[PDB]
Length: 201
Length: 201
DNA sequence: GGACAAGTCT
DNA sequence: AGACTTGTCC
Ligand SMILES: [Zn+2]
Ligand SMILES: [Zn+2]
Image (cartoon, rainbow over the protein chains, first blue to last red):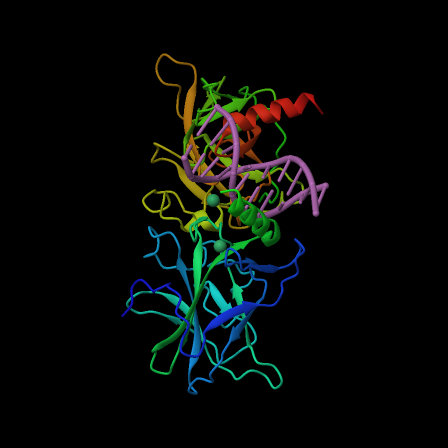
């Protein structure tokens, strides 16, 4: 019963926040994150490991959801899905358990469930929260983005926001992280150009 | 029974040759033809009228066939079709009587038949030959191209040639014209840029 | 990693 | 029409 998913950040009572693994500063990296602009640059299909920080262990059954939304307040009501060209292309959507209409996927997990809202048609992927591996404190989730930010008919060059929520079994929103996501072929140069464009402006 | 349609020219015993009309020299023209390079520049979907020079009246039932082929000797055997993106797009392929997979269409003609080679898969559109309208010497066919020369999944930035053949009822190739075809959003500037890149090379 | 290429915004 | 943008070649 939520048409326009709320993008506004909300650190849950468990200090909800997401960070990233020092993506290779080189222009060759398959992904990179800009904390200044708070935007994630990722190559299509290429795996993107996300660090999730949890300060208070949540009630078991609690899960994390990833949902793509549109940043353009004019397209914010439109559902984000894979490109119509990519929705069919046998390259990746032919052997994966993930539906070919979902933009975001999760690599390396079977408990991951892909859901299509019946009333809102919103695509999203959820995974039950896992305890940080022995020794470390952050948990890691591997996400895939099966569409460039420029694909024709899908997200026609219009930016998006990735909504990572921390829900419980019934669906109560506890923590909510958000960041703009740009999927391109050269995440490095695009990040650089966006930061330099950020200063002199 | 022709896998790799022959591209080279072959005037028939009816002096087979194609020409064009005004070619609004301005860069705004939806289409423009270069006789120097012998290449056609056209905007996607926009109508391109082709003048067919018929010399000796051919046998009744004779038809003309437009077929797109790849100029790259590497992709030549690959069948040219609309990009998977455009094959779905509700833009044009939703109310037209032409298959959503065919690159070349004919506008303003119900006698036009769109055929897929069952053994080769080649797309092509055939229209029965019409007598030059009263008074004039040129018969005209209105062709449409529903895929840029840069679309994704289809003819991705690799050039093509348009094969216009004059066949009879059974299919004997009487006349065969050919010219490279570029579908872009700025046919004027691309024509100029190619014609200048021609001498400085 | 630089530069060409080509669709689109303004 | 000029120029930006962004995927892709080299
Ligand atoms: Zn796509
Ligand atoms: Zn197309």
